[PDB]
């Protein structure tokens, strides 16, 4: 589970940076991309805190904060996907992003039900 979170953390950073290449496709998508990148950056910081402290030692309040954050990001990622539907490449990144965010959710879902 811990090793799985390290790999998902790597995904968060990768796809957050990959979203920066979608800039310039449309002015309507700009603010959606930026907000998503900044929220993902905050979530990565939170997952960094979780790993360094220890997943077995995480309090319920922390897990609730993390679950709240990832679900909001997942909703916003879905909205980005819907708006996108260069364009094809953006959809591929958005698709892989969604999958990675779901993996992050499943880690936290498992920790919360432990």
Image (spheres, grey):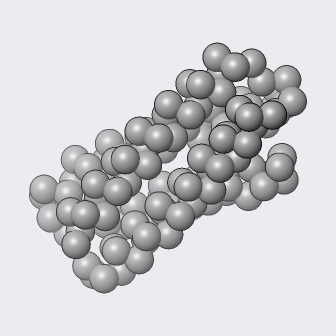
* Residue drawn where x is 83% and y is 49% of the image: 1
Is 103 rendered above or below residue 61? Answer: below
Task: Decide which of 24, 60 is in the foreground and name it.
Answer: 60
Q: Position of residue 27 (x, y in %)?
A: 13, 58
State the count of labels: 0
Which of the pair 110/56 is nearer the observer? 110
2 up-or-down from 58: above or below: below
User: Residue 18 lies in what quarter of the image?
Assistant: bottom left
* Whole-percent x, y for residue 33 in the image: 31, 53
Query: Residue placed farthest to the left in the image?
Result: 27
Q: Residue at x 31, y 64 (%)?
A: 81
The answer to whether 84 is drawn above or below residue 48 in the figure is below
Q: Quadrant of the C terminus?
A: top right
Looking at the image, which residue is at 15% across and 64% down?
26
At which x and y percent is residue 62? 65, 21
Please tell me in which quadrant of the rendered image residue 66 appears: top right
**Residue 25 spot, x, y in % from top left:** 20, 69
The answer to whether residue 24 shows anywhere in this view is: no
110 vs 70, left or right, is: right
Q: Quadrant of residue 94?
A: bottom left
Q: Is residue 78 left or right of residue 66?
A: left
Q: In the figure, is residue 35 to the left or right of 51? A: left
């Amino acid at each position: 589970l811990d090793a799985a979170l390290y790999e998902i953390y790597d995904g968060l950073i990768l796809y957050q940076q990959r979203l920066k290449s979608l800039e310039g496709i449309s002015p309507e998508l700009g603010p959606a991309l930026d907000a998503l990148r900044y929220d993902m950056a905050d979530f990565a910081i939170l997952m960094a805190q979780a790993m360094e402290e220890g997943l077995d030692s995480l309090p319920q309040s922390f897990l609730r904060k993390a679950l709240e954050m990832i679900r909001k990001i997942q909703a916003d990622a879905a909205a980005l996907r819907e708006k996108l539907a260069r364009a094809a490449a953006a959809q591929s990144i958005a698709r892989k992003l969604e999958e990675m965010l779901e993996k992050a959710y499943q880690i936290l879902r498992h920790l919360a039900a432990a």
